[PDB]
Image (cartoon, coloured by chain):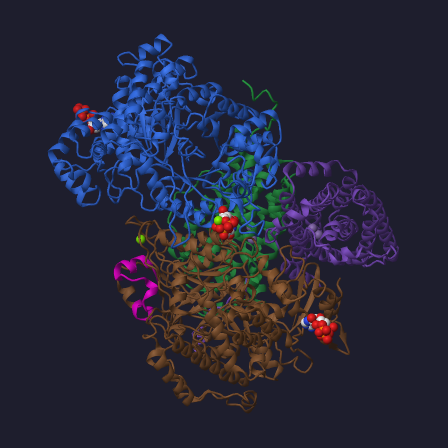
Chain colours: A purple, B green, C brown, D blue
Amino acid sequence: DFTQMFYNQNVKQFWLPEEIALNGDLLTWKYLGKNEQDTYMKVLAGLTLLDTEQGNTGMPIVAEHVDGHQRKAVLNFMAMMENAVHAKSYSNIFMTLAPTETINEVFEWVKQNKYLQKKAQMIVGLYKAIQKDDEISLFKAMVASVYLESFLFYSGFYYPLYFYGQGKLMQSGEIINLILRDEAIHGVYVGLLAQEIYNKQTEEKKAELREFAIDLLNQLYENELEYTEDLYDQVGLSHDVKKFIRYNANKALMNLGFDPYFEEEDINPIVLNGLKATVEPLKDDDFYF
Amino acid sequence: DFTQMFYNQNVKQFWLPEEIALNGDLLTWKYLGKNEQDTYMKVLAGLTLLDTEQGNTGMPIVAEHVDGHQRKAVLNFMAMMENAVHAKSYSNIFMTLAPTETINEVFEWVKQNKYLQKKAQMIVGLYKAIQKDDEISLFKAMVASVYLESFLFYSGFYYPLYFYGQGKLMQSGEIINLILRDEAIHGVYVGLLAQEIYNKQTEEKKAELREFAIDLLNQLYENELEYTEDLYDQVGLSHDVKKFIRYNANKALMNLGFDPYFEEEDINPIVLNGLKATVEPLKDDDFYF
Amino acid sequence: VPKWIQLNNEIMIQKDGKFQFDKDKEAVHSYFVDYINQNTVFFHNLKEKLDYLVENQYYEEEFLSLYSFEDIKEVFKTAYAKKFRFPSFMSAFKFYNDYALKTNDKKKILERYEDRISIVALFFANGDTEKAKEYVNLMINQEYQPSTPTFLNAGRKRRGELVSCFLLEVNDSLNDISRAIDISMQLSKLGGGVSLNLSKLRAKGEAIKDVENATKGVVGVMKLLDNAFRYADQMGQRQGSGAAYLNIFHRDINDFLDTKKISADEDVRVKTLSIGVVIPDKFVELAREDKAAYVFYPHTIYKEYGQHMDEMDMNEMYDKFVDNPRVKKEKINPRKLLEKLAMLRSESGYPYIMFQDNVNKVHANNHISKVKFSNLCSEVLQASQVSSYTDYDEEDEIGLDISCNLGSLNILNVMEHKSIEKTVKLATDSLTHVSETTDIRNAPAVRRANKAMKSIGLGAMNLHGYLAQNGIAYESPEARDFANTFFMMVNFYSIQRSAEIAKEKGETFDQYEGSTYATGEYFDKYVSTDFSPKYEKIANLFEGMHIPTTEDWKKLKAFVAEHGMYHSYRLCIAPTGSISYVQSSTASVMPIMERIEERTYGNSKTYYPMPGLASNNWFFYKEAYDMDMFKVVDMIATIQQHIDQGISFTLFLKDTMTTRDLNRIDLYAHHRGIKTIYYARTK
Amino acid sequence: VPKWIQLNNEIMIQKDGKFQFDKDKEAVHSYFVDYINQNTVFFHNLKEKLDYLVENQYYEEEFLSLYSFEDIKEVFKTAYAKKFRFPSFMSAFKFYNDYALKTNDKKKILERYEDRISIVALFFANGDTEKAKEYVNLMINQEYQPSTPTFLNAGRKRRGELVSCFLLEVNDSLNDISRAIDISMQLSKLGGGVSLNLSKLRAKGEAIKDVENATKGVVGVMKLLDNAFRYADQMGQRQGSGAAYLNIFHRDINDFLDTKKISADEDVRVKTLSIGVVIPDKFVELAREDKAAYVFYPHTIYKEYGQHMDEMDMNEMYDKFVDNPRVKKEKINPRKLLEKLAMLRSESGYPYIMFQDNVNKVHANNHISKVKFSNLCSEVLQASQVSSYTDYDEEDEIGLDISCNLGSLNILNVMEHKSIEKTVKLATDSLTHVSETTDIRNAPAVRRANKAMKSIGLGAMNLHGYLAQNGIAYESPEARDFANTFFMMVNFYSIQRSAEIAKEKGETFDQYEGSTYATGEYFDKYVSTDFSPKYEKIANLFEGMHIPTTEDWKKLKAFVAEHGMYHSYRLCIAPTGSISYVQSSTASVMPIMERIEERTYGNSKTYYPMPGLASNNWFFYKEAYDMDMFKVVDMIATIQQHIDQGISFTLFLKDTMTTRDLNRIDLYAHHRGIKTIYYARTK
Ligand SMILES: Nc1ncnc2c1ncn2[C@@H]1O[C@H](COP(=O)(O)OP(=O)(O)OP(=O)(O)O)[C@@H](O)[C@H]1O
Ligand SMILES: Nc1ncnc2c1ncn2[C@@H]1O[C@H](COP(=O)(O)OP(=O)(O)OP(=O)(O)O)[C@@H](O)[C@H]1O
Ligand SMILES: Cc1cn([C@H]2C[C@H](O)[C@@H](COP(=O)(O)OP(=O)(O)OP(=O)(O)O)O2)c(=O)[nH]c1=O
Ligand SMILES: [Mg+2]
Ligand SMILES: [Mg+2]
Ligand SMILES: [Mn+2]
Ligand SMILES: [Mn+2]
Ligand SMILES: [Mn+2]
Ligand SMILES: [Mn+2]
């Protein structure tokens, strides 16, 4: 009942980072403190890693196991967006704002950062555990994917949105908003596929799947807290970001058909402010009136 | 040396089925004989069936085994074009020209056809034989992929190009020309990835891989001749189609860095009308001599 | 968020199922109680203000020295006696952000609306205190609005030129191309939009000094011009805007068009250079009959006939070009070219379309030259003569380069004051003064044509606003009847004022004797067809105003025959981008795009309803995209029959309609006599 | 494959472990007995050939009309009496593909080597049969080679200009920038390489009439010039080549350099415009002391002092610039800038390096102007005065834009014939004739400088060929001794010929009286130091020729004081790229890049051995990349001490060495007095 409308929405949202000129951010970037620039680079690098694995591994593997040519076409399109559009856009931002050495250093930093490695290990592990014709392993990977789309990106998204909302780094911010618009529909779509599998189960099996989903969320959440503190303490924003990730965790649960898990909190209003034609030939009768 | 350049060329060639209005083809379709309509339907179904294998297996399997983030992104983009763009385009052409019952029957026929099946299963067999961390099996699959993209499609493309060059079925011919333009670049790109593997091999292993490629080409070519007579004798075109197959076989070989196998032939003019040094700081005392 | 911005955003908040339009008025008050008055520099008296502005190089001494201080004070008092109030927040915001004079530090406001209007009036009058007061009453009643260059820069020492539409002819030589680049840079430096005719330039693959396949075509010239316009960007304030026009029978026409395709490479696409295509009737006839057309190499035609391809009538020359073996040509499909034009306009709104024969069958100055191209806004249509810029230490042959003087009547304010005649004549006088006071020392042909032709463009705006506030649909026959009558009166009084100025000064425009004004042909349709309203509602709208009859037009024709006409061109309807906000008017004669427009300034959102929009006239304020483009074409043709130059005519398309619909609109515009088509804005 | 192609490829097929160099000779025979003699056009006699070439617009009839046909026949007979044979296949191939005159369709050969030499000699002599025979003997012996423009275009109707390089000074104004673009297009149309000094243009973020942060800097002008050179590309035959020179103390120097970075964005990257950097001694001093330097805004300096930043000595005004609060400046690290220069030269071979103080400490015409930039090949170093191109209808102040005529002595052939004096004097006369008959009607400053300065460039080729064929290592002190003596002789006889021309014409170059030639300072090192060879082998090499002593130099100094000098500049050593093939000579005074070079022509490949390469002199033909760049710098400085203009000094680097090695080579070149550095070619 939904794939065709997601297909149409995904293809109509198609974009490339080159559509957005980035040289306009040069001055507001220059004006940020060293702490702010450091957090910003690292935040986008963490996002780049997530999209790299979502494009290389997550979306293609889910596409392989989901039945139906149209469902596969949507998932293939989403996979392309992850690595050919999203992951690449971050390099466009980096290449504009930062010198090569700072770019090299931040990519070295992703490799050695323990929270980023842990979250990649956990998510990719679940993707690679999918067994052919085994719907339960597939469900588990789809939960992981929804948590990546609708929860894990948000510790990263906070900062570009926080600046966009203050009228700073608005070109980079425009790219990020386009990425976020895509991930929101990706999280909903994968969520609907996960619910399909969940709804086939006995009540006993469902109870176990909810346990899996909640245990996984809590494990990812605890790691994300440490990651958030590590990045944001130097810019004074860790508590604010934590509220934001809890907000988005609830959205991820809802995408999976589950009740919200965290209590509602006031999000920084700045971040809230941060949010060819068809051709016919000419007939001889079109020349007369 | 080449992936970013191909990335650029691929993404700038992006297109969607909806851009070409198909209904005006009915004004020339109605004037074709039964044999012409039959051949066109059968050719179209042949292309559709082969392209589906490439979207579901060929491109995603190569993307899975190739190392490199940028290569995986380009390959993902190509897989997307197969599944999201090409497959929808072929379906659109069919739905415009034939009623539902006729489409189902043509696909039943082509699905049972000996020559279409022989080539489809030969290609799919090589994709299924790729082994993790074995570059020889990957190379063999890449050869199969290049043969599909740059050679096997062309016994089929001939007919739409033949009409397109005569002013018949111009809307579907425009679509086919866009598809063909994508397959050409797909073949060239996968060809470069195969040459990379080939160049890492010993001289004896190279000679063995050359023998594999020529032997495979021979098997496919002999089946193409039979496929060609089976479809094109009823419309009197087989002689010219055979010249077009050999010409495209030579292009496929050149994509794999191999010499042409067949003598140069002229092609039907109607079809032609359709077609960093180490940075070391100054240490002082370098200013004194 | 400031208080006025909250009061403005409260418009969208619906009370009793209705938009709170009146809240906008409150916003204006806030915008003046909280911001404008606080940041407005006040002086003990006007003498101190004028001394401070003159001494600090804000104003010019020359125009103020023509009056005694008592006369200037009287003009300012006349401006302030109206007690003018901006009816909407966006009007005051646009004026005080774009036109009000600010200090060098851009934190204080030196000029109010009345101050700017008084200064512009004093500049217009050139020493006449009564004329200055008349101009002040004209602009404070908002009946007439000088263009953005004139309104912003009149009386200011730190200013650009008062003309911002420039049309350049480029001759087929490297010296002429370099001179065109230089003149484009100089005019963009002055703040003007520059349009260049590239039809005389020989196509790609032509001979230079009898060596074959040497010319780069017009695309290399377009790349040079695009770089020149990027470089000259008003001292880094606005993006340099330029236009290039090519005849559709030029061979480069495809490559020309290929400069606007998204798939075009970096060495092909020009980004800051608008493109327009000139389409003679011969191309439309060839496309209509489906006969294959020929695009010609201009240099071969020039060598064979001694004249440029765009300098002769293609209707009578096309067969001779085709049958001439010494003329090189390439086969094209005119219907395919039309479809390419429609597709390009769908993608990017380019190119502008100029129907050459539609322009030239009513052109009054065909003896001087036929109109070969238009301006950056595709509404200036004047005779131009190419210049022969020779080598150094050699005398150049200076031709005529078009530069008309913009100014717009506010149709609502003009008609509610029953002052069509007075407003048109005063606007003509102001445009004549600005044209006479324009002296460009780096554009020789522009200066020569300004001195000789004395061409001005008197436009109109708030047509849709006036019609909607009077219960008239823009597509209704009553709206076209009103446009016919109103613009016939505008043309009548513009011609009368031009003839009166010619009689007073004793001089006409150069080569007037060969014009259709001198021969009386221009007045033919005016001495035989009565343009009085055919509907009682429109006649009641025109109540209290004398509507010129056929006898009045005969008297005007005799007056023009006896005394001549001072201006070669008088009327052109410009888009009127930002001045329509300050005047609280709809832009140009175009229908409104949106009933309420949402804009983002800084990090704040703002809401501008169309002027006079309410629940009663919500239906009459139909959006342009929802309208039938054929009826919009009919209205624009009705207006164009009374406008000597063109009208900036933007097409408003839905995303559903295809290139066939765009081509049909273009062909109906050509059939209905539309001279230019500006843009294809897709919703 | 052709027979001569196979014979030429037979060189690399070793026989008994040795290259088959003699096979090359066979190739030439084949190339003549199978292609050239069959493709040549023969006439009954010389009269029919000359008539056919004159009426068919191949030759200018004016220069041939100065001689009776008997004299032309005698000149051609003198040319053919030498029985000149090309010793290598590539020499004849290069002549008959690049310089021999062909038909309009380029299917046949109209000019032999003797025919081309005779035509060039007849053009040079200007009606003197004996002088024409002297030129014929000079060129057929290959003692002197006119530059590619002169050799290719002399006496041709369809010719371009005979001047190879042009240097333009661009003043800081939009009018001057547009004029510079126009002149660059005009001179690239004429075929010459154009160099523009952008140091006077104000940097990015400067004020254009009191509105600040308005200028685009030198990068916008660079983009404009790049597009101009792309458009004017010799009618699509040879890519338009331009050079931009910027002082290292310009604020835009980084952005300038960023135009050549391989990671530069498209809005900044410039690809057809070479870049050069002018480094005063102050910058090297600051980098040596590791003191942070300051780059300056030219417009602030011009406002404060009334002169341009590059118009005065930075070594004495840098501290005043830094301590002046009214001068705007930015802090830079001079060592980091040097490392950036080295990295850029490693990556792309750019920028050209011009050591301004090294040029101006021996510059003879500092009174006219200091040398502020170089040409596209970084060997022309002459005084230039910027032009004030004003508005239209205003008189322009025409300055001096550098332009000199190139001509190279073949060192091997000159010394074999023991004719340094005669060859130098005849080459000076030919270059004087080329300057006199040069008249450019679209570059006023170039024309005025050609008429006033009368500057010529007399280069030299086959230095390494002569040294290797005489058993002298290019890096050896004996080679530097030979270069010292030979180029002192060349300078002596060039000065003597210039003074003799000044005496015979009664005129010197403009402002000669203030030059060091007039005051006698130029001859100081020549009247106190003896430049005779210090080695017996070099003295034997110079046997049969009178080496000037200090007494001869004193007599020449007295002669110059009495009569003056006709040429402001006489000697400049150009790269001599493709014409060195025809002369069977190594390129310029540079060491050979490779012993045998493999070049692909069409679908075939050819091997050109270095002239005279054999088994006995294989190791004397040491490749440049294998050589110590410090000893090459020593050689170039030894030659430069006798050359008034610069030398195109290409650095030949290995991939293993770092940017620190490149910086060390640059600093040693600056220490040794090297004026300019051309290229950093990495193996
Ligand atoms: N809508 C408006 N348009 C223009 N100016 C306005 C507007 N509202 C207020 N102002 C400015 O603020 C001043 C205060 O106007 P207000 O509405 O308070 O009463 P007033 O009787 O017009 O006042 P005043 O004594 O200033 O004439 C006006 O004189 C005018 O300068
Ligand atoms: N290396 C070369 N350089 C220039 N011209 C050459 C060369 N080789 C052959 N030719 C030309 O081709 C002709 C072929 O003659 P070739 O050199 O074989 O000797 P020939 O017939 O005995 O006469 P001669 O040597 O006296 O000209 C020459 O006369 C000359 O015009
Ligand atoms: C007009 C213009 C100038 N410039 C720069 C380049 C020129 O070197 C420099 C001088 O321009 P000028 O032509 O000298 O401008 P001006 O004479 O009106 O201003 P001023 O009195 O200060 O000299 O300004 C731009 O960068 N962009 C532009 O659009
Ligand atoms: Mg010409
Ligand atoms: Mg100036
Ligand atoms: Mn993503
Ligand atoms: Mn996603
Ligand atoms: Mn496909
Ligand atoms: Mn494919």
- Is residue C453 visible in this depiction of the protein? yes
Q: Is residue C80 magenta?
A: no
Residue plotted at (45% across, 57% down): B161
Question: Farthest residue toward the top?
Answer: D536
Q: Which residues are magenta?
A: C295-318
- The vertical placement of B214 against A160, above or below, is above
> C17 and D275: which one is in front?
D275
- The vertical placement of D260 against C284, above or below, is above
- Is residue B169 visible in this depiction of the protein? no
Q: Is residue C141 left or right of residue D523?
A: right
Occupied quadrant, residue D502: top left
> D11 and A262: which one is in front?
A262
Residue C544 is situated, as x and y percent measured from the top left of the image, at 55, 89
Magenta segment, prevailing SS (helix, strand or loop): helix
Q: How many marks?
A: 0
**Ligand 1 quadrant?**
bottom right
Residue D314 is situated, as x and y percent measured from the top left of the image, at 52, 32
Occupied quadrant, residue C673: bottom left
Q: Is residue B149 left or right of residue C598?
A: left
Q: Is residue C316 magenta?
A: yes
> C652 and D643: which one is in front?
D643
Q: Is residue B226 left or right of residue C282?
A: right
Q: Quadrant of the N terminus of chain D?
A: top left
Occupied quadrant, residue B86: bottom right
Residue B196 is situated, as x and y percent measured from the top left of the image, at 55, 36
